[PDB]
Image (cartoon, rainbow, N blue to C red; front, side):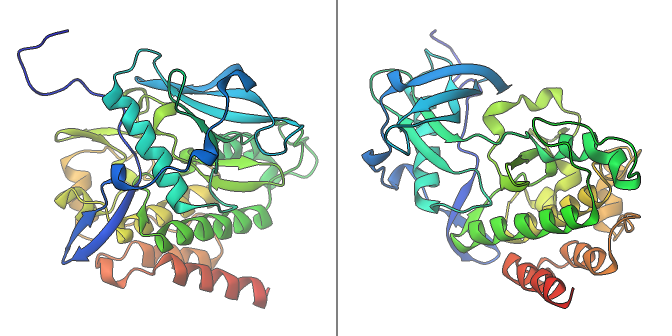
Length: 332
């Protein structure tokens, strides 16, 4: 209804950013509304059947659905559908349109959650993406955790996957996520919230980097902390990024280092037991770092440490990380 303050209610926002140029120092981003939309993506909404909710946030949700003829003309497939509230204002719907445009611009890669289609006419805006049957990687690591150190106990069952977790899995996830992020970086794209909770797993134990924002309300997740005017994933953020309030290619790399730590720690939360407050920010800026997880190979811990270099310029690029891990594989 009518309000007497200009500041608009919180609404869904586009999550990933595309960089136009770095003149600094500072980043200038592309305005996503200016990107094209190809109507080849348009899918008759009557060909969707909605199932269970996968995750819901304050503004909308993502649901499991079946789609008929979406990719192969005479076949049904399971997909994930992103939606706002049915009466969402056009300005909020436009954020979903901009998201659709960014996904289209990025293009397809095995290690992201890919765009499959959209319903932008004839009703509430829907974005159709890949369904990842095993859910998020953080939960997967936690369910499978006990099997890493026991070969007698039956591994936790997740859908059809009754297999144990081993070092080969962790090395594979490390490599896959690095490739996915190298892909995003190659398109000048910044994720801003890379973490195990936002990486999904599908058939073949393939990891897919996700934009999960619509599917949770961060007020209910203690890994997001009030810091100034925002609630932020501070334990995954680079110190200079927290201080200057800017997300960069180098701060995504910092996050990948934190991801490697939680990966080889089998789903433990970072800086365990450490209060997140004035003292935490100070200690990280002054050089405090986590030590190696028990299960992390030395070369992976070494990558972690470089991802956490106080100087953003000295951190590896994702391209360089991919090369390093591929060197590991060849020598293995």
